[PDB]
Image (spheres, rainbow, N blue to C red):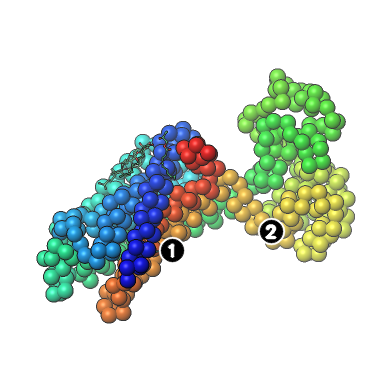
Amino acid sequence: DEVWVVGMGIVMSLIVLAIVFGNVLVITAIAKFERLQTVTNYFITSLACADLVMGLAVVPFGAAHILMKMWTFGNFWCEFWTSIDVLCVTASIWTLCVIAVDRYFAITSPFKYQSLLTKNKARVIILMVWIVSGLTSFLPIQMHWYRATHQEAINCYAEETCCDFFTNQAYAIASSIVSFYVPLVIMVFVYSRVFQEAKRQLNIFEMLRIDEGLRLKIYKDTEGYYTIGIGHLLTKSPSLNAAKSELDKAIGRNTNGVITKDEAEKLFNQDVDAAVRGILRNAKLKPVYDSLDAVRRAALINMVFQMGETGVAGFTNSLRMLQQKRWDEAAVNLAKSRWYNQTPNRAKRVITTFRTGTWDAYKFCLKEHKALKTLGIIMGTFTLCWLPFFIVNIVHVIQDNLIRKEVYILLNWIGYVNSGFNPLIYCRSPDFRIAFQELLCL
Ligand SMILES: CC(C)CCC[C@@H](C)[C@H]1CC[C@H]2[C@@H]3CC=C4C[C@@H](O)CC[C@]4(C)[C@H]3CC[C@]12C
Ligand SMILES: CC(C)NC[C@H](O)COc1cccc2ccccc12
């Protein structure tokens, strides 16, 4: 009906604007902001370019084909539009596959969160991705290797008013495997390992940076004490000069209340070392430390770092339950203390770690780990949007009558909307948030 055409036109127009303005904002943020110029952000630029080309040259011509119920652009632009459409989908999943592999080599290296590729090498990878995917998309379509031999297809090719994607059963299987399924199986398997390595490689140093935080300026403790860096207490006295005196002496320099990232790490490596030293000295804490595994030993050091050797020793009943490998009974007594009431969010994480003996409580807490979850959402959404289309595409090869034309176009458009979702998912990263609000002048 008339109301269904007007309504569809408005919706389709807003989808185009969201994809164009959205991906324009992403590319501009990376190109101007110095901190956003990383190897990982170079692959995101490749992904944003494909979504922008999709919203300017693919989605507009596809919208006109639905509203007019005919093709008014000829047979040359039909085959060229189809070639660009495929190239955009092929390059996007292969770019997401390269990110999964690069993030694996980085997490398994001593650099931990830095790509082993240079900015010059990454530029070559992105260029190779587009050149190779450009050949597998344009050549089988322009050479007419895709064309079906049935009468309904031959008539559509000859007609200048028909641009319906009719393919031979050989092309539909070969082009789906190499363009979509091959990078998808690799991307899923490789990135499931990246999430595994990150959780497994968590230590006491990463644990306390989550609980205590990192501040290079003298701040106020939850108990009103003077603190600097990763939970390093300066003094109990309410004197900023005495707090500056304890800081200026410990480093042996003119601090003036401000310290560097290299200086804060130097103090932390000494505090953790002293926390382990205190346990071996204490006769009540030492036999508990020996009966605990690697994960649970870190949970005890965390308590000593916070409350002190004498403080933790006061949990006479809880320490006994930990020594007898009774985790849930120790957990109830630890909850019934002033420690749980002072820092509930921190104590909840330490007590759960004593119960499970895993890093389940510190899941995606670290800033470097949150960046891995963000990339994981991008890969997940892309799979959720394009999988129903490619599955129905393979089912159509087995049995032709089961899938209707109206079902095919609807599933293809779910994949089209995905080109406008990626810029919204980049708002998870604080670096992009500050860049987006600057470009929008907010
Ligand atoms: C529709 C077709 C014809 C257009 C294809 C656009 C091509 C030329 C685009 C898409 C993605 C682009 C790349 C995206 C990311 C970067 C990182 C930057 O540090 C240097 C340029 C480089 C490597 C771009 C070069 C050009 C590129 C390969
Ligand atoms: C309507 C048509 C022009 N849209 C094409 C899709 O959005 C992209 O789908 C595809 C992408 C890559 C390979 C493929 C092989 C066979 C069939 C479809 C493929």
In the image, which disc is placed on residue 80? none
Give the mark toward the camera: 1 or 2.
1
- Mark 2, other Cα within 10 Å: few <14 / some 14–19 / many ≥20: some
Residue 335 in picture, x, y percent from top left: 81, 58
Residue 5 in picture, x, y percent from top left: 32, 65
Residue 106 in picture, x, y percent from top left: 48, 45
Q: Secondary structure at mark 2?
A: loop
Q: Residue furthest top?
A: 254
Q: Quadrant of ligand 1?
A: top left
Q: Which residue is mark 1?
A: 384
The quarter of the picture where residue 326 lies is bottom right
Residue at 78% from the left image edge and 39% from the top image edge: 221
Q: Looking at the image, can residue 386 be seen?
A: no
Q: Is residue 80 left or right of residue 106?
A: left
Q: Which residue is mark 2?
A: 357
Residue at 54% from the left image edge and 56% from the top image edge: 196
Residue type, numbered disc 2: Gly
Q: Is residue 239 left or right of residue 346?
A: right
Q: Is residue 158 left or right of residue 97?
A: left
Q: Secondary structure at mark 1?
A: helix
Residue type, numbered disc 1: Leu
Which label's residue is closer to the chain start, 1 or 2? 2
Q: Are marks 1 and 2 in contact (CB under 8 Å)?
A: no
Residue at 36% from the left image edge and 36% from the top image edge: 120
Residue 69 in picture, x, y percent from top left: 24, 66
